[PDB]
Length: 46
Length: 95
Length: 48
Image (tube, rainbow over all chains, first blue to last red; front, side):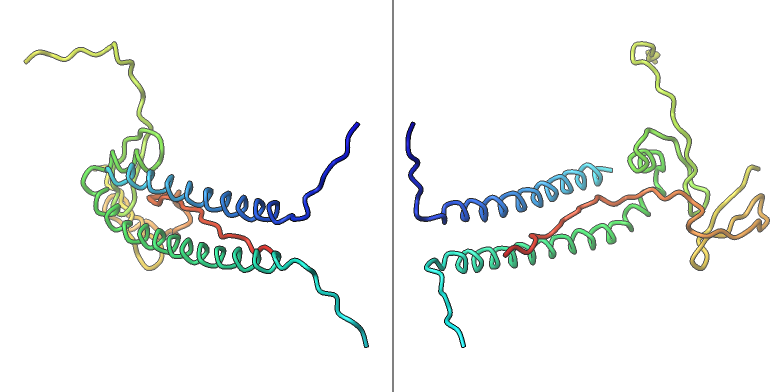
């Protein structure tokens, strides 16, 4: 058995949430931009 | 009358400011990218119109998705699917 | 021989066969391929 110590600051968790949200969205949009750029080049080869 | 209770942590507000700034800027830049992409496509439709008149086969094939054979009937393309042939069954004549 | 052409006219097309007017058509009556590269850019959703 043991006892659990809780940190008095939650700002690590909220910071993690904010950064995760921004990272996920920016990564998604940039992936779409990269894929579109790739398709545009493969498309203008003609 | 009442009394107002104030939270001892302001990190919600600063987090809101940071996220709002990033959201606003990223949304602005991505909107500009999307609008530019739209205009680029609407702009290159002209090149695509004037390339299909050179050899409709390549344009029609890369556009439809399959490997089709096409010709132009005025302002439209008439297509027909092309039948594959195995690689090993070809002979190149020497002369 | 075999002549048949569509021509852009107004907002639709006019269809001729064997050098004789046949009939008009709307844009919807023809399957539309696309020379466009899709870019589905969404936006950072609001968060509070």
